[PDB]
Image: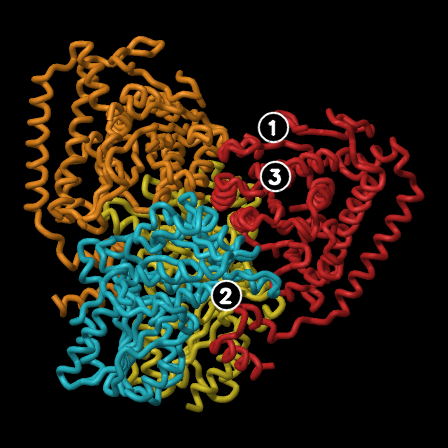
Chain colours: A red, B orange, C yellow, D cyan
Amino acid sequence: HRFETFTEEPIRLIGEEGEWLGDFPLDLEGEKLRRLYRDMLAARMLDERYTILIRTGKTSFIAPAAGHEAAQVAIAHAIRPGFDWVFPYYRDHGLALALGIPLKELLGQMLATKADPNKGRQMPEHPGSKALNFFTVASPIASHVPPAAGAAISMKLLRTGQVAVCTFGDGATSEGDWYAGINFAAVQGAPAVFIAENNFPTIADKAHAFGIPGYLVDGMDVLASYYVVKEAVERARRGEGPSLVELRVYRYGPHRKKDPIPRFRRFLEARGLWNEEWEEDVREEIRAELERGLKEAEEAGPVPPEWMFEDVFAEKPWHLLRQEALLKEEL
Amino acid sequence: RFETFTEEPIRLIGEEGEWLGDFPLDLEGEKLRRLYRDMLAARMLDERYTILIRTGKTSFIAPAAGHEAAQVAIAHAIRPGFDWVFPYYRDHGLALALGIPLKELLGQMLATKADPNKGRQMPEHPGSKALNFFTVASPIASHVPPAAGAAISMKLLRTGQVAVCTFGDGATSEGDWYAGINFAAVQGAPAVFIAENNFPTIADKAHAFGIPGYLVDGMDVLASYYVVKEAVERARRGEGPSLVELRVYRYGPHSSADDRKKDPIPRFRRFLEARGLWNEEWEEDVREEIRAELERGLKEAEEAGPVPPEWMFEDVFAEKPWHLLRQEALLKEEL
Amino acid sequence: ALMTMVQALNRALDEEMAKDPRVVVLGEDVGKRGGVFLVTEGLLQKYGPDRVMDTPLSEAAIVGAALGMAAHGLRPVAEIQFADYIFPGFDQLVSQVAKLRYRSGGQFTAPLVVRMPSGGGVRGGHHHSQSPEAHFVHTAGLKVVAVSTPYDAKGLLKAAIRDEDPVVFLEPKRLYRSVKEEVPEEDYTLPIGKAALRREGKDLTLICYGTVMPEVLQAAAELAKAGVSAEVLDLRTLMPWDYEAVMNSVAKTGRVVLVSDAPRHASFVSEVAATIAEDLLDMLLAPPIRVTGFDTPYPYAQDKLYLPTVTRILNAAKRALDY
Amino acid sequence: ALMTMVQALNRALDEEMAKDPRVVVLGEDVGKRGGVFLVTEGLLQKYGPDRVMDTPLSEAAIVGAALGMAAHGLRPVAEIQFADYIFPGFDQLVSQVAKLRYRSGGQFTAPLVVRMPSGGGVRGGHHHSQSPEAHFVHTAGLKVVAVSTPYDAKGLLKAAIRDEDPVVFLEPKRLYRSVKEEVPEEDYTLPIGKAALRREGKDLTLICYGTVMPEVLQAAAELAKAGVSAEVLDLRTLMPWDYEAVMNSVAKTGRVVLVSDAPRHASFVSEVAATIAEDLLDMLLAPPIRVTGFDTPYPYAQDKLYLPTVTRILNAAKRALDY
């Protein structure tokens, strides 16, 4: 099976009433389907939690991702977390959660506490995890695209069988580095999948510039997003090169009938996979997970001032040693 | 209108010098002969550069033999002195056909005072204010964004001008190439981006901008002229940019330091001959005229004299600040 | 009347655009939004999309297109959302903009302005707090200006727009609305290349500009309580910088501390310091001391400490005074 | 064996590649071409395309991919055809490479080398002569090395390849084959961060590196004839630079002249000079004098006047000695 490339209308698999539109049989067991829904709720609730954190001064910056749940959760499940690599952008905290990154680490980073494995080095919405191959977010718009290409090339040469997925907003597709990076991966037939979380010439059409397949998908459809990205991942994994997948979404918050959660709920419901009771049990479990995560993150403690001189290099050279000694005089 | 994104490059001159276009040929015999004349001149300029390199009168050349059809076609598809050109280091043939004096081209190659760019850069970096020939910059694609900007200016000021931007195949790998063209497309700017591709096609990349892309036989001066011309007219009427790929075969090496049956010239010669627009005697004369033009241009370039050492401190800014005045004074104590 | 830096900057743009049709503004969200900091607010509504244009999110495209516009016929004022984002457009800035007049023997010029918010003091982390001025100063062909007051903001931005040489205009974001100062509504400009004497003194010279002004001025105030009169010299223009102003002050006081939030190594203040030592060794009563950002990327958590504190500046002043 | 810098570099690469499968070479025309300067000649033939790979002509793709490769498991040695062309890949260099270890709390690293030919004196005009080292030294997180002899070229490149920190390796192209020197075939490395004494002296200190070494050593030779004993210190590593070697030398002679072909303003030598004035004012008998490239784009016609001349260096030395 192969989805149609460069379609005029975005690829959909879920009807507005829970019907399956695929031209291939659904092969996700009931448990995995419910798992997708579960993660989407968690991502949504995490996002709403951020709104409170920012409102109550707990954090200085948030990048609302409500509306990206289908796209972000789909990507997390289309790859092997811990094996494949992810080169995310600042709006991917939902993807990070679905990937398995501890809430303690995501929140530790949002609050810049010692719970942040990135040591509060950057502003909020810059998570990163070595454990889950989640390349630490960089502020620039598309600076992480060439690196993703490089990682993929490394996977090809070293025959690891891994894949590197790279996400970005549509604004990023205007940057030269976006083009240069994907072009290199295309030329090398590198196992990289470039995904646009487009808050909607399409972006998929740009794939023509690289001679790689381009896909326009309904980013509010978790199954359409899952299957198209998964196919791209498999293509990459078998050595057939990169793909550009455009997942069209709609951001509710700042930079109703489309909400991906209700749309997928109906799909589960139509198959005896959902009911109000389960819904509440899950939400309750999630809010408990969130409170526990925030607690651990907060009581982790502020990051030490000296840490400002750590990790510039493997070891602190003479000038940094002198600068750290200088700062101390003031502490 | 020519077909966009074609499988085979667009061609108008047959193997036996016959016309292949759907429409009838509408260029007068005089214009056709002019195209050939300019091609010969461009070719002979290139061969003179080889000699300049051999005797070390210049330190660097970027062979353009094989680009004559593309470069001359471009020069004639636009309005020299009105439209703008954003060239790259291999466009000396385009420069010549556009009308830039040999004195100035050779002056820049030899770095004498005859160079309006004052010997500031290494060879193959011509530039002419009078003919809107944006001074060449070494980087492969750095002139693409500027080209888009000038086109945007042409649009805002309703000048009715067009900006053509030329570059090689390697430039299409650069982020700035993409970024610049994308901005021009988004703005619907009157700019034509042309690849002189020494052969996904480059034309296909046009889909990424939502602009028309053309694959053309760059060794066919008529196909190159007509397609580029169409792109230019489209831009001039405010319909936005286009990407034109002129596939060529460069004869010489990528570049040189002081240490076939595809040649566009014979191909067009055959076309003119079949129409009574070419004869052996006319070519002997043309070549003699050109040789005379070359030696005269070179002579004037050399007699202009070396650029003064102090010129090194001029033009960094409109006026020299204290630190440059200081540095200049310092150097003078060494002269 | 009294107005913030944002208002003064906005006034300067409005005034220059009303005076010259060629002046145009371009950048990410400079139109409808009026800029992320509101510097261009209301300009679109007043002058139209042909004078104030939103562009794709490409700094190479912005800077490069601005260069093309300036070479052809416009007087573009391009905005880079953050100083940290100038990098994707760095080749355009240094290979095209800075070298145009020089490489063309003067045939082509670049009357354009690239403005950008910079410096820390607001918790910008890695790409919301940088001060990259050294990269520009090191590049021949670019004038560089860093303002610190609403009065200067308007006077110098207007001056930049009239200047034919390319000007990189840095606006410390922490100062955008940190103070409402008197700014004449009448047309006036300030000279590019000239420092401003913020406070006269005879015991110590404090060389500074932009982002760090708040801490330097308060430092001078603390020194005053102890009877030490510090002379505060806001350079304003970093290229070409006020050689005379600097040397006059230093010769007088005999002691100097240079302050900035840009990383220490190969920074602009390092240039001034090396120049003071090379030219006025005989007038120095103490070593030229530099208080700058540390040689590390801009930290989010320790943002408060990276930016020179009043205390850090005083420890350096004390060191220079006791020498 | 006696070899040129090119051979010494080529040997370093061959050796490290034979030793570690993770070491890969990538850049424009590094494969079958062997490189525009032949530094990578024969490597493709010996190691194959998945070890020596030609890349698209994009500096951002080269640097960025290298970073991605280094972060994932390879030890890439990337080549930027000319130092002048690093700019299109500047954001990748300073935003991704330089800050990766720092912004990730040490979770991710960048064991990569970025090689690039640099310096003037080769009639390279604006884009075949630049010495951009300052841009790198000013960027926290990047180590910077600039070699001047075949022996150092091999020792330091091997060192760079083994260093886990990102290293920007500048190779003055005018010195690629300027001389044949003894280079041990055996495996040996050199310490990054350590200067090298080219000549011992006590009347004057000559601080320099890279491109200008020929004229400096020559200037020193002429000072000797005149009874002046100058000490020549080749920094070799610009970041982190040999602080002690510099201060010990200057403390002894009391007079120093710094030489480089990089533009003066905010240059690396300006950093060293400002640091000398700040830390050893008491040991200075004369002002720190800097002999640098002029603050202009690199001129073609005046190529040999832009690059410091022995005369220029001698004139500076004279002022230091006569002070």
Disc 3, SS: loop
Indicate the quadrant containing the C terminus of chain A: top left, top right, bottom left or bottom right: bottom right
Q: Which one is in front, C136 or D194?
A: D194
Badge 1 amino acid: Thr
Tell me if I can see residue A200 in this picture: no
Q: Quadrant of residue C284?
A: bottom left
Q: Which residue is mark 1?
A: A5
Disc 1, SS: loop
Determine contact: label 2, label 3, CB under 8 Å. Answer: no
Q: Which mark is residue A39?
A: none
- Which mark is nearer the camera, 2 or 3? 3
Determine contact: label 3, label 1, CB under 8 Å. Answer: no
Marks 1 and 2 share the same chain: no
Q: Quadrant of residue C65?
A: top left
Q: Which residue is mark 3?
A: A238
Q: CA distance from mark 2 to mark 3?
A: 33 Å
- Which mark is nearer the camera, 3 or 1? 3
Q: Which one is in front, D67 or C268?
A: D67
Q: Which residue is mark 2?
A: D165
In percent of width and height, residue D144 lies at: 41, 66
Q: Is residue A83 above or below residue B105?
A: below
Badge 3 amino acid: Arg
